Amino acid sequence: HPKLVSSTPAEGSEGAAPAKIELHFSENLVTQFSGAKLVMTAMPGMEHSPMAVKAAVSGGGDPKTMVITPASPLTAGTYKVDWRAVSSDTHPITGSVTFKVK
Ligand SMILES: [Cu+2]
């Protein structure tokens, strides 16, 4: 139900891998447990066995703007970009952005 303000990660981005994940928040201010992590969970083959990818999280010009940039190129398949936003009031907001790559 709860989701960040606006972002451009890869909302069900099926067709090809994007350049970088984008995130925006009118009240980011992490300093809690906010972040992001990309996991390559291609089609179900090994009893659903996800794996974290070698990526990094870096904010844009503003600190309220997040920009995920993987050090490695996203190959075809399926991936899930799990992000977590939290302002300041316990109960962190969790979200995931799945996308395909062809
Ligand atoms: Cu709130």
Image (spheres, grey):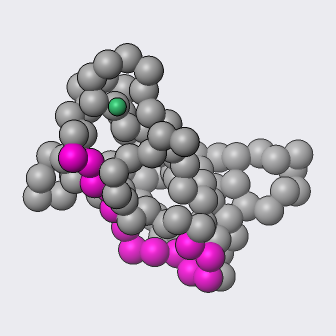
86 is higher (above) or lower (below) than 89 = below
Identify the main secondary structure in magenta. Answer: loop
x, y percentage for residue 86?
34, 31
Residue in the image at 57% along x and 80% along y: 16
- Residue at (70% x, 46% y) in the render: 50
Magenta stretch: residue 74 in it? no
Residue 49: image quadrant is top right
Q: Which quadrant does ligand 1 occupy?
A: top left
List x then y, in percent, for residue 34.
36, 33
Residue positioned 38% across, 47% down in the render: 4
Judged left or right of residue 80, residue 32 is: left
Query: Percent position (x, y) of residue 88?
Result: 27, 23
Can residue 53 be seen here?
A: no
Residue at the extreme left of the image, as rendered: 61
Locate the C terminus and report the quarter of the image it occupies. Answer: bottom right
Residue at 52%, 75% (x, y): give it. Answer: 17
Nearest the camera: 50 or 33?
A: 33
Q: Quadrant of residue 22?
A: bottom left
Residue 31: horizontal and vertical position, in percent?
24, 25
Q: 64 left or right of 69?
A: left
In screen coordinates, is 99 left or right of 38? Answer: right
Which quarter of the figure is the N terminus placed in? top right
- Figure check: 52 above or below 101: above
Q: What span is in magenta?
A: 13-26
